[PDB]
Image 1 (cartoon, helix red, strand yellow):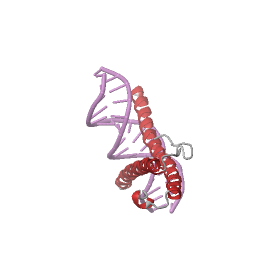
Image 2 (cartoon, helix red, strand yellow):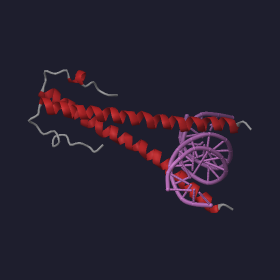
Image 3 (cartoon, helix red, strand yellow):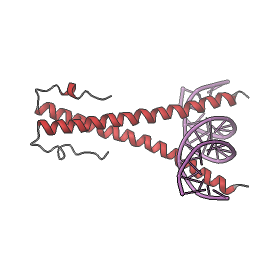
Image 4 (cartoon, protein in one colour):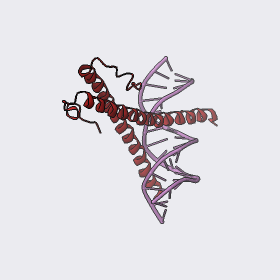
Amino acid sequence: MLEIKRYKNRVASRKSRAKFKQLLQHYREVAAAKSSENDRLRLLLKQMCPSLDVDSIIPRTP
Amino acid sequence: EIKRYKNRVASRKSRAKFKQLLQHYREVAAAKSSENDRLRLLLKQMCPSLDVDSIIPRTPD
DNA sequence: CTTCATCGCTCAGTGC
DNA sequence: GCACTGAGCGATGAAG
């Protein structure tokens, strides 16, 4: 039939759906890494310059 | 006859929900990364004499 | 005249 | 009895 057109197209759909899914996971990991670094940074700065409205000059992101 | 239409609707909903999630997390990633940059910045201006890349290494991105 | 990336419809399972 | 989703199949819209 069009066996080869179909194998190619099936490979392509599996590629692109995997692409979006891993990109979503990737963001979730970047968010994770970031929020953790963020708390470390924020607490260290609150420690060091305790006369600064840190959580106001850089409000937390959700 | 009907399972067909209702299934079409749910498949629309699935593609959308997941695009919404990809967007939401796409955004949270940028928000936290900019916040990370400004915190390193402000710590480097308030505690300049101090090494933040060995207390709190950057995670690439 | 390829070659590829998305995505919409459908079907078959998969968890309410 | 049902909503959700992984996946195949054709469009469709580029890219060369």
